[PDB]
Structure formats: structure tokens, C-alpha cells
Amino acid sequence: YVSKVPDEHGFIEWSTEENLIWQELFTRQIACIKDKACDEYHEGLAKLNLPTDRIPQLDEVSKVLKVSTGWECYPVPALIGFGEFFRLLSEKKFPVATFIRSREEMDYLQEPDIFHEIFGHCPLLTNSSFANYTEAYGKMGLNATKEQRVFLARLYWFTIEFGLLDTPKGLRIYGGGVLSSPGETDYAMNNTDVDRKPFDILDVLRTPYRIDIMQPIYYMLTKVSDLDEIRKFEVDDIMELVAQAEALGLHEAKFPVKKAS
Amino acid sequence: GTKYVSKVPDEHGFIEWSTEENLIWQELFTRQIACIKDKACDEYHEGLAKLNLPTDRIPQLDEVSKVLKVSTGWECYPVPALIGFGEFFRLLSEKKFPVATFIRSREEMDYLQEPDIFHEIFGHCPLLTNSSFANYTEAYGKMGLNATKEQRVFLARLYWFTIEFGLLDTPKGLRIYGGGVLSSPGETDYAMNNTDVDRKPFDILDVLRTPYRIDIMQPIYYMLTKVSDLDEIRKFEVDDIMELVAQAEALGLHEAKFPVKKAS
Image (tube, rainbow over all chains, first blue to last red; front, side, top):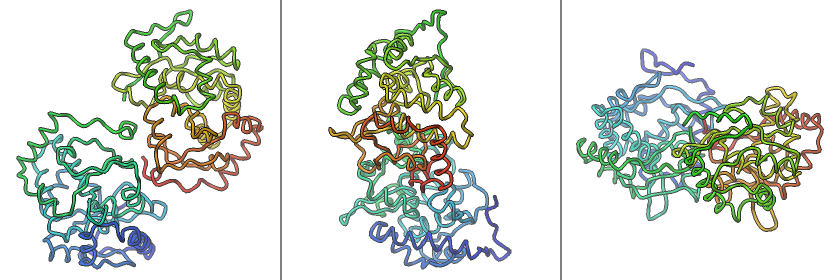
């Protein structure tokens, strides 16, 4: 009912239980991602040196993001609008909700909590290609319209949230929504009937999706630096791509999307 | 989606379907018969032979009820697009199968939340010609007549895993009897072919304890060996059923599958 507020020193107090909850998400995820999270992500983990036994203070993460890519974490207490989401991202500020799930909601909850953001999303923010892409993504949305922003959310979904890699050493994960969750990691890596497609930006912009279902489609880069290609595009090029997508219309929804409310 | 309304009948209970509505039925029928040819169970196919449904127009309920009456003593019973569990259990207990008299739009051809007339008659009616299934359904209606809200959730779960999404482990392979699978190419493909979905032998307590969500692809299905396996549940007194429900309540639900946890 209340997501925490930092004190006058920006410090947040977490109960030993909220620290035990973090520890348990951490220990179970470290196990889930050994040979599955991309190398780039593991490198980020090493730079971050996150606490395994308690929730880190935001400044303790930010100070590593700052030195690597110029990024910081940005505490948010309520849910923010799209405009503000892009504003923060274009300023290389990554919004971080200041709460952790209950034990009851440990395997899944819908609002991204502190574990989701810091474990799933922040390691790659130490990586220049990913951090630059995310900044570029936030710039893409500043002036974009309601419907253009819908297309960009979709690009976001398929890269930052649920992105995969097709590597010589096999399939890997870079999406934050996958890396922070045993359920998602196992499905993304192991489910044999899900479509896994090579990344194509027009394909992506045209793909319908629903958030509360098992994803029937994923898009695959070869390596995280591939995001440079999209990062390089001018905002005009991106809106051109959005318009093209609109002219062709969305792909037909996969049956589980059609089914979902 | 779309808000649907039952068509109002004659006074003789005749419904006028448009050529467009009848073409929509024909398309659904033709694409579905092809799907289920080697996938629906024998008992279902025999139900279709008994119903001899028109392939190119929507049947009048009377055409269906005529066969149901002959075979199991059942009848189609026209109802609004939205009815309550009170009415639903009641009509079932009376061997009255509720059918909303509408068909889906072209745009909702591949899927819709509401059971339309194709869902109801094609998907659900053939097995009501089958004494084991019809008798079971009648027994299900009866289970619900004096059920508390809490009891009805458990009953809806047995319904879900049997009548709606039931499968069989047969000597010729995996087959479908669930009316919510049969009426749909997407459900039929998934139930038959998906590699990773859990298909478990039927156990009434396991079933009563199984969390589920209606707008997701089902992570679990339960298999009888034959439709007549339903006779065992049918035979239980309502007290026996409610004992099983009390047992499930006391034990609590099985831990949900990840997709169930994830669902709205």
C-alpha cells in the first residue's frame, strides 16, 4: 500500500525479512542464470558486486553505473507516466521502484520491484552498448505521440524486457524481465514450442504482445553490441520505421495473444 | 471483444439466421471437422453421428433437442448471452442444456470469451448423446444446487478439467473429449501437440486442488482412459463430493504453475 521513501540522506531501511526475501530471490536466480544470462550480463554483475544477503542502497549501485556509463538509479515511489519514464531515461536515470514483493508474491508479482530492477536490469547498465541504447530509447519517446509510444514500448518489450541472444555457445538472455525470474529463464531457454526469431526491427514493431502471458515470440540478437545498430538510427529513422509498420499493419496475433484479455 | 445478444425465437421457437451467420457456421464446422478427425475421442465422433448436424447452416435447437431427448433425455434450452451459476447448475440438474442463441463475428472467428452457438452445439452437445457424459453432467448440475460460493469454485474446477478441457489416454493415443478444446483449432493443436504441457492421469482430489486461469494456454490437463470413467464421479453422493471438496479446501490448492501465478 506504500512503496518506500528515502530519508534525508537518501537511505532506505529494509527489515531483516525484506533482506531475507532479497537473499532468496538472489540465491535462486544466481543458480538459474549460470550458463544462461549472456556474458555481457555476467560482466555487469561483477562490476556491480551486489550484496547477496541484503537489499543494496541505491547510491551503492548508482556509484558503479556512474563510473561505467554515466548512469544512476532513480527512486520512484508511485508508478510514473510514459513522459516521465522517457524523461528519466534520456537523462541516463534508470527509475527504480523502492519496494520488494511479499513472500506470498515471491515467484511472481506484476509491478517491477527492487529485485527486478537491480538484479534484472542494472548489470547491463554498466555495459556501454546497452546503456547507450536505453538512453537513445528514452530520447526516442520525449516528443513521440501516444501511438508512436505504443510502438516504442513494443521495441522495449522485445529488447530490454525479453531480449535473447543467438550465440555460438548457444541461446542466452539479456532481457531484464527474463533474468530476474526462474519461471521466465526456464521457459525462455527450454520451452521447445515458443517461437524464437532473429531480430528485425520492422518485425518487432509489428508484433502484438500481452504482458501477463507466456511469450509466444522472442527476438534474438547475436550479442548485446548489436543494439548499436538501433542506437545509431536518428529519431526520424525510427518514426519512419514506425510509420512503415503502421502502413503494413500489425502481424496477425498468435493464438495466445488473441485469447488474452 | 464484442457484446453478444441471444436471438429471440418464434413463438414456435424458430430462429432466423442470416446467410452470413450460416456461412460463419459452415466455416467453423469445415475447419474444425478437419482438425479433430484423428484427435477427438471415439465417443465424441459417435455423438456427431447421432446429432447429424448440418454443415452449412446453424441448427434450430429443436433439431438438436430431438436427438438429445432420444439418446439421453436431454434438451437444448435457449438462454441469454450472460446466465448465473444459480441458473446454470439448475438447468443442468434438470437435464436442460443452456444454449445462448448467437454466433461470433467474423472478427472474433479464431477466438472469443463467450460460448457462442458453435461452441455450445459443436463443442458441447455431441457427448450429451452419450449416457456416461450426459449422466455425469446431470450429476454435476445436482452437485451445485446447494453449494456455497466456496464450494462452487471447486465445482467449476472439476468442470473445467473434465467437461471443458478433458483429455483421454486411449489405446490408440491421446484423444480429446473437452468441449472447450474440440470447438477450437488453436485449443485442439495445443492440447494435442504442445511439448511441455503437463498431461496428468485423472485424480478427483488432484483436480479439485488445481489452480487455473481461463485466458491462458493451459499448463495442465487431466486424462481419463475413456468417457465412461466419468461414471465413477457420477456415482458419488453430493455429500461424498462435498467431502472431497472439504478435503481439498483443508489441504489448500496445489502450488500454481508459473503461468497461473503470472496471469491477471
